[PDB]
Amino acid sequence: AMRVLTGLQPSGDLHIGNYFGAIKQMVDAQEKSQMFMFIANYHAMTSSQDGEKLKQNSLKAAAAFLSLGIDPQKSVFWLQSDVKEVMELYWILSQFTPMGLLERAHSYKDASHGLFSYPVLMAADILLFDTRIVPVGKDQIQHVEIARDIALKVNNEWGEIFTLPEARVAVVVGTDGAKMSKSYQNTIDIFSSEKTLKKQISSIVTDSTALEDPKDHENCNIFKIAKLFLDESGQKELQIRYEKGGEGYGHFKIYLNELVNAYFKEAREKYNELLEKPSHLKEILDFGATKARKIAQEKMQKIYEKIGL
Amino acid sequence: NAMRVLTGLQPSGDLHIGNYFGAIKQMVDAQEKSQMFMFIANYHAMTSSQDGEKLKQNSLKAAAAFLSLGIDPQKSVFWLQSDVKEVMELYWILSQFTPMGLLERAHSYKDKVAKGLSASHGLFSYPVLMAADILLFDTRIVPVGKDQIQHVEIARDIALKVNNEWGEIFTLPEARVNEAVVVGTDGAKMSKSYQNTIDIFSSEKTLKKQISSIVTDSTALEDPKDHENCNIFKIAKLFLDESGQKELQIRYEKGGEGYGHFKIYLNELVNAYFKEAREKYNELLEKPSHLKEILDFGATKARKIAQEKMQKIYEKIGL
């Protein structure tokens, strides 16, 4: 079984696209492999230097992933900056990185040195742990390939010291029909207040269809989100309500509201428990950092032989 | 009230007479009334070479050489760069405050790109690391060479950026360009590049070769010799006090001794002058753990200041 490593964005608020799209699958994969996952809070600094906001974002990211089912016993789960080894490997990988490689990168292309450089720091996270597989999206594919390129450059020079990582890649619709995404501001958040959740579900864009008539559920965003929360029978019963007529889109929102609350009630409660007693969160994160620091310290020793430390 | 002076010492190359009468003696003598921080810059060395076995022994040799020439771990803070790891982290942080054009215009990179050669990310980024070195220790003065000053200006710009954003986090550092030239074997200023050096930590054989290579006029053995023009006399002056040097020109202006003999004299002068350094040098490498203890001590003092500084930083970045 291959080593799968995921960096996790601390920034922002987790939404149900994230959940049914990435996380749920990842949480169910914790049995067939030792997963490694980290809140990349180092990368978070390229786009912000408000410390207090960054700090909170990390605690909150931490708690959110745990409550959605990351089990720190099965997997290796930690805060990036807790394993400082990556920082020194970053420096070493830089010496093997041609500028051109970075100039042609895409999050920069598409301007601080942090922003230009972060692909090397990413290669360091990947390479430090002999990652076989990096689960990403299209947007992050060439970052993985850049780490693989750095790896080949180092191997040629030092012998095979690094595993060559390989990138691995059904849409949740957002509020407006598009892919749900923070950047489109069309999301339904998981850890928000009931009041905020009702507002988000209210913004869902609908047909003009009149309350009295049959509504098309095949093209209704409300029905598409709801599909995520129901089996075939619950989906049939709501389809029958669309067709029958006599209920408005507003009635369906109330229903989606209750579906979304019920579904995440536990994760929400666990989240709040984690943030009310943060000494437990720290402990979970410290425990994950220990397992990762042990793998990292051991790769580093081998690097140190090659680089003379 | 002695302001903090910080100097990065390159681990590569062989130290020579010029390195000593030129820069090192002054640094060693500054220790008493100055507050000196000096580190062996082994992270920077990594941009030039990735050959670990060489890099390690250059680092050791370097540390042993400076200690030998008079760096006092008790008066000073002296350490190997890589022993104080906070510096890597500060390097990441400063990158967030470092504008690209500030690096695209750095000489080292510019000039590399001009020749037509390709550049590592390391080469491009080293100015930020350098700036982390400077700023991590609240450096007041960075002793610098006539062309190296851009480095300090870069740190100074990053410093302002961060302070603008977070308040008084950094002391703004200042280049101090240092103040007689040491003649090389060929008459030109002695430097590694010119291959005109007389090394300090060499065999008796290698010293003799280098000294014997010194170039001279064809003033015959028996005839008076113009000291005021001889390179042997120029160099010999560095090892000799007032009476010592006059005693010697008397030998020149009397005739009777030839340059071959003066070269023999010069050998004994250099050998004697550096004997205690050379023997100290050899012990530190032969008994690697006395060296280690001293570099650990140094690293311990540097690390305390770096930690007090990273504590401030951690507050502001949320770590």
Image (cartoon, coloured by chain):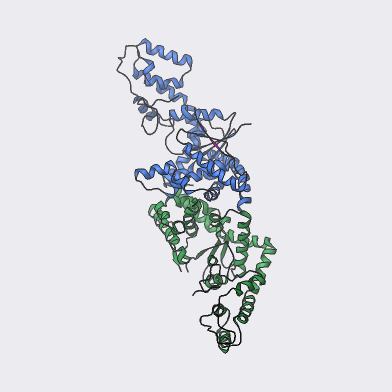
Chain colours: A green, B blue
Quarter of the image containing the N terminus of chain B? top right
Q: Nearer the viewer, residue B53 or A237?
A: A237
x, y percentage for residue A132? 46, 64
- The structure residue drawn at horizontal position 62% and vertical position 51%, both measured from the top left corner, is B316
Q: Nearer the viewer, residue B279 or B60?
A: B60
In the image, residue A125 above or below residue B62: below
Number of marks: 0
Residue B188 in magenta stretch: yes
In the image, residue A144 above or below residue B87: below
Q: Residue furthest top?
A: B254
Q: Residue furthest bottom?
A: A244
x, y percentage for residue B188? 37, 26
Query: Is A238 placed left or right of B127 in the picture?
Result: right
In magenta, the rendered stretch is B168-196
Q: Nearer the viewer, residue A211 or B82?
A: A211
Residue B270: tell me if it is visible. Answer: yes
x, y percentage for residue B22? 46, 28
Query: Is B258 placed left or right of A303 in the picture?
Result: left
Q: Nearer the viewer, residue A147 or A297?
A: A147
- The structure residue drawn at horizontal position 59% and vertical position 73%, both measured from the top left corner, is A203
Residue B318: tell me if it is visible. Answer: no
- The structure residue drawn at horizontal position 63% and vertical position 47%, both measured from the top left corner, is B312
Quarter of the image containing the C terminus of chain B? bottom right
Label the magenta part by its dominant secondary structure.
loop
Q: Residue furthest right?
A: A276
x, y percentage for residue A58? 60, 60
Residue B56 in magenta stretch: no
In the image, residue A26 above or below residue B278: below
